[PDB]
Length: 43
Length: 43
Image 1 (tube, helix red, strand yellow):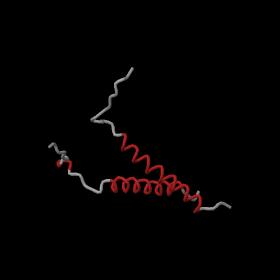
Image 2: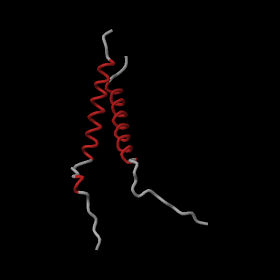
Image 3: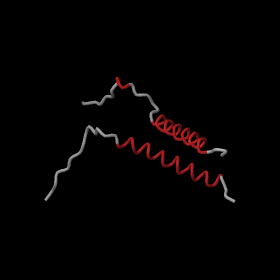
Image 4: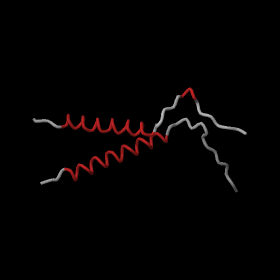
């Protein structure tokens, strides 16, 4: 019987999906807020 | 008659990834703007 196996070398770390979302959410928000701070001025 | 069907097994390109990011980016932005429209009323 043939069995499938993952690449240990890769050393996958889960949850992976949570990282993908958390990563984009952080950059998106951090960028949105930061970019907005520069867009807002007194003059 | 009939035509042969082929496909990429190795799947070099990373289209799935583009979907994950595009998906979050859309919801994040769409939500940010929408939420802002209701969070900020106009005179």
